[PDB]
Amino acid sequence: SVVGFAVDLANVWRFPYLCYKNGGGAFLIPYTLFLIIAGMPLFYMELALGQYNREGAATVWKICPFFKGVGYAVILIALYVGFYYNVIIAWSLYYLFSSFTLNLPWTDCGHTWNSPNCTDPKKYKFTPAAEFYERGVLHLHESSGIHDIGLPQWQLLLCLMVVVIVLYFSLWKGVKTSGKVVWITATLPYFVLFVLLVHGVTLPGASNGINAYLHIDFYRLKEATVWIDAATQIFFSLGAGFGVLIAFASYNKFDNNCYRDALLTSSINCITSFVSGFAIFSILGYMAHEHKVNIEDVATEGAGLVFILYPEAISTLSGSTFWAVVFFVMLLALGLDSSMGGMEAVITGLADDFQVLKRHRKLFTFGVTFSTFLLALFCITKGGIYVLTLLDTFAAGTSILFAVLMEAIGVSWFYGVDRFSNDIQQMMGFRPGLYWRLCWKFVSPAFLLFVVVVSIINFKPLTYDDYIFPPWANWVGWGIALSSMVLVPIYVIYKFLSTQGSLWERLAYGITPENEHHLVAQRDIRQFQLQHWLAI
Ligand SMILES: C[C@@H](NC(C)(C)C)C(=O)c1cccc(Cl)c1
Image (cartoon, rainbow, N blue to C red):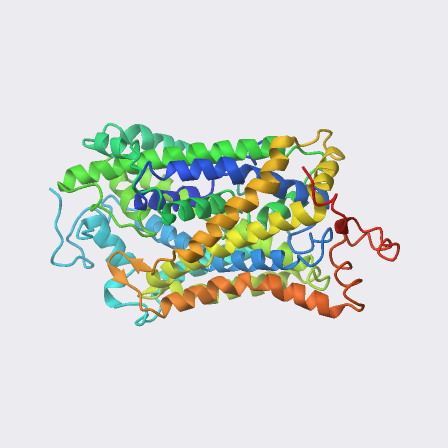
């Protein structure tokens, strides 16, 4: 129905600035290839696991112990990502509250936040829109670096509090009963994107942007950054690896098809990404023509690209207040939907392990939301964009790829792809097929391992638009990244130590399904013969 139209904030906010940073059309090849190779198979696998096991993300490993750390890693990654996603909803709320006027604040250089170097056009950042973004919302000119953070800005704290309160009151009494937060997330993004796409092709100088978008230069390939970014964006926008798909599938009809769900979700994700890229590059070409500069020196390459691009296109339409209000309401709805999904995933995954948290939902929800608010207090300071840049690089970078790789390895090699394909035939009626099984078993681990190894080997020091972080910010970032990657060996060691027996009865009590326990004494254990390990 309308619950398959999964359009996320990572498709409207994050894809545009990753596509512009990596050249343009030289970014869609590693994206589409990675989609085909590993996004659909893993989305299918996650949907099938969640549907069949009828449980959350951390207690879903009742089919194979020694692997519960994969759930605790994706529970922590979800937390880290919500400490910075709620600051992009606060920005949207600030812009929406500033949009209620007949003279938009991002059109003139005669305000109190304008530097005397403001040039009206009639990396830069001396334009009215960039000046507004960097000096009236962020107040970044009062910070010198990550070492000089400053105090939180009250005008953004008052917007963060509203977001936190809304999230808590939407999550405090069970899950939302559906069809309340998505009947507008489904329709509005497509209408707004269509209007922007049809309007932006008639602007002067948009042809250059379109040509730059539909042009592939191969020198940008053969470099690690494009492939790493494409893989991370796939496993950020498809929803896999965050533990949300399993929790969502845990509440569903048993015989609901997931083949069609996976195909439709992937196709719509690709279409929306392509349309967003087209619109963004058309606006970029327009601005490049207006300022008489190249298309590569006209806009920032950071996380605030849309908040400088989209207002510029809005200010050219007829009735630029109605459209601004519509666009920012759409952004707010998308952000609220994504935050609700992530927080629900966390709460369910933590309340399935322990039974004392299932009768204290108010207190637990309050705890999670208040922790998120307190930890997000760091990103609304006068130098919070640096912290947001650190967290948007190291919270789900190599760690998410490692988690997905470990989950795929675990399932396909230790539980058995034969059993995985035999319990899907038991609940749908058809056996997956050769392509899906081969894809999972051999093609997903290989490419995921290649990406992880290349990312570790070819690391690049962190920078923000000519600003170079001190050499300890990278250490802090790697410490954040390894905080979830280390939970997998630790749980294996603890589980191995906590049981009793020899090497046998310990290596085998944590590799067989929990239900299949009274066959260890009989020694009827499949994983030890070679014919388990030659699955097709
Ligand atoms: C992966 C995706 N989650 C959905 C619900 C599947 C879209 C997401 O972008 C996210 C993940 C964790 C936390 C937050 Cl706030 C957002």
